[PDB]
Length: 260
Length: 260
Ligand SMILES: Cc1cc(C(F)(F)F)nn1CC(=O)Nc1sc2c(c1C(N)=O)CCCC2
Ligand SMILES: N[C@@H](CCC(=O)O)C(=O)O
Ligand SMILES: N[C@@H](CCC(=O)O)C(=O)O
Ligand SMILES: [Zn+2]
Ligand SMILES: [Zn+2]
Ligand SMILES: [Zn+2]
Image 1 (cartoon, rainbow over the protein chains, first blue to last red):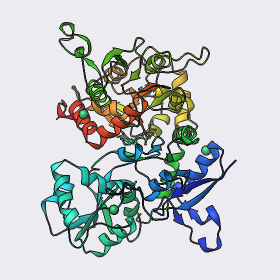
Image 2 (image 1 turned 120 degrees about the horizontal axis):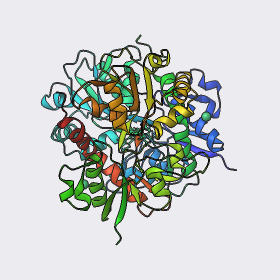
Image 3 (image 1 turned 90 degrees about the vertical axis):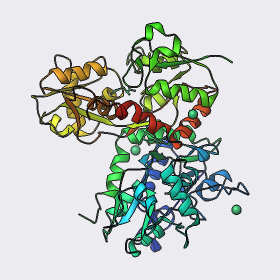
Image 4 (image 1 turned 135 degrees about the vertical axis):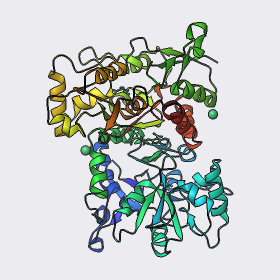
């Protein structure tokens, strides 16, 4: 009936521009895990769709003062998109305003270091000051630290919120580049999925250290009242049970892996 | 207003009879992860509740011929219970007939061996005959194998469905006992959570081997149209984000683990 507007975000390897994208049009410009997922979800739910990259390049957070949502969440809330198919973390504040499918991928917050950085844990980071560390802006990881009552994470947040120069970054790519150029003096807090991906990318100079700080998942999000909610939810479960989600993770993370 | 009837299942360490249960009343008769979780869900959602143990001791399957649901799923479907708070796996066939919250615990199907069994993977099991293997006789693990189109799992199902005497077991405890008494000649396919629990129980003679075969979760289930659906879902998210779910796992799996 109507073309479904999918909001997504340029985040490797979920959605990336193809090497030859400039000569391509519409959905064909993009590739990645979420591009593949979107095609599968659309197939099983029987809709046509248009992939649109989120205008402000953000996942989604609510301004404390205006109460206005930004990012992909904002696009859903304000009716600019019909569905978000992205590595969008299922969170309480978000699930209060949009609906999430069952998770299509699990993750937890993790630590990325430049190889050789003498840091093994969140506790290690919190104890010292020589190595700076931060998170992505307008995402679920920043909110995790902001809200945490756990002493280690509370101390980390107290440090991060005030740190000069700013330890927060606008994009995951910015966080990763920062780790890579900072000679071991910057650690980055990011989701395990993204961390593991980057660990298998040239120049193979980063690694994930320590356990995950939490356990959660990404979900496909729809605005409240969406006619797509049930079908999308069931389609995620179908794709999981077919082993398709695992196949896609292997395709985008490890099959193309550059670090041996 | 009205006391919420909770269906659950006697499965360690989720729900267990307290040693002194005969001298206790109602909800106080039980202990475990899901007992603790039920109390917290009820507090956060503002309802009074009565724990009940599923009459038939099953999780929930639909009979192929009668189309009747058994187990906890049936208790929800047929209106015998208002909510299931148990290690109940989120599956497509169940989500078609009941609602699940977001997952409160992650798990995958996994392999339990008697220590020293020369099995490292599902592939290993599928390629040999000396070591028998089976699943819980009703549940999502059996269904995974029944429905699988992946070669290794198909081969396994082909073996399991035809094996005489039956490789299937009535309860997890029966599966574990069978591994323990079979001198390495039986391996049990069960959820990683249950596997990890038993690995920390005396006599410390079993272990999880290989990676998980899939990735899913347990959810709190409510019948369709339940007024509890949203509150329960948000309560799971709140409890995850506040670290309670991880605390409860540690409490019931590891804090009093018997294997060092
Ligand atoms: C990969 C997969 C598919 C399925 C499903 F299909 F069964 F739903 N579950 N999972 C595992 C998963 O994502 N776990 C999740 S997501 C999530 C939480 C947990 C958890 N703590 O276990 C806690 C609240 C925030 C959102
Ligand atoms: N997946 C996160 C963004 C990345 C992060 O915060 O680490 C979100 O949905 O906000
Ligand atoms: N958690 C499973 C039962 C255990 C199993 O099948 O391994 C279910 O909900 O069916
Ligand atoms: Zn498909
Ligand atoms: Zn503002
Ligand atoms: Zn509480």
